[PDB]
């Protein structure tokens, strides 16, 4: 009886963790490239300063 | 995947914080754009009058 619902809980945890991992995968590169574009704005804005 | 969740959380925090400093991020490199603007006549006009 403990087995069945504990396995249910672990499957739910696996699904949730997969969701959050896939989420966290994107935003890191997202901020990477958006801060990159900030630098670019500064990169091409070496004119100013 | 759990640990890598924090691995990427720290990285995203780093990017978002460097992107939350400069305004959050970019007017530390623009806001004196106002200066490159005003000093146009702040200096030239300051000397334009005397010239």
Image: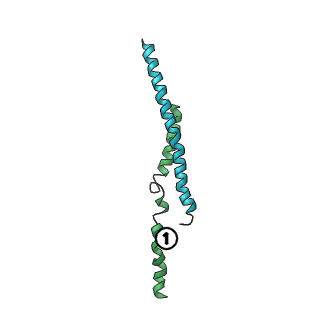
Chain colours: A cyan, B green
Residue A13 in the image, given as x and y percentages of width and height: 46, 26
Q: Quadrant of residue B23?
A: bottom left
Q: Is residue B5 visible?
A: no
Residue B34 in the image, given as x and y percentages of width and height: 45, 68
Q: Residues within 10 Å of mark 1 (few under 14, many from 20)?
A: some
Instruction: Tell which of A14 and B21 is nearer to you.
Output: A14
Residue A15 in the image, given as x and y percentages of width and height: 48, 27
Rendered position, A3 above or below B41 = above
Instruction: Tell which of A28 and B4 is nearer to you.
Output: A28
The subunit letter for the residue under badge 1 reads B
Pointer 1: what residue? B36
**Residue found at x 48% / y 76%:** B40
Residue B33 in the image, given as x and y percentages of width and height: 47, 67
**Residue found at x 55% / y 56%:** A39
Q: Is residue A36 visible?
A: yes
Rendered position, B14 above or below A41 = above
* Image quadrant in which the C terminus of chain A is located: bottom right
* Image quadrant in which the N terminus of chain A is located: top left
**Residue found at x 56% / y 66%:** A47
**Residue found at x 48% / y 32%:** A19
Rendered position, B37 above or below B27 = below
């Amino acid at each position: 009886a403990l087995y069945q619902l504990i396995t249910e809980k672990l499957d739910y945890s696996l699904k949730v963790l997969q969701e959050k991992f896939h989420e966290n995968n994107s935003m890191c590169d997202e901020l990477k490239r958006k801060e990159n574009n900030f630098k670019n704005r500064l990169k091409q804005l070496t004119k100013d300063y | 995947y759990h640990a890598h969740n924090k691995n990427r959380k720290q990285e995203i925090d780093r990017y978002l914080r460097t992107i939350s400093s400069k305004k959050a991020k970019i007017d530390l490199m623009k806001l004196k754009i106002l200066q490159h603007c005003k000093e146009f006549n702040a200096r030239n006009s300051a000397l334009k009058k005397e010239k």
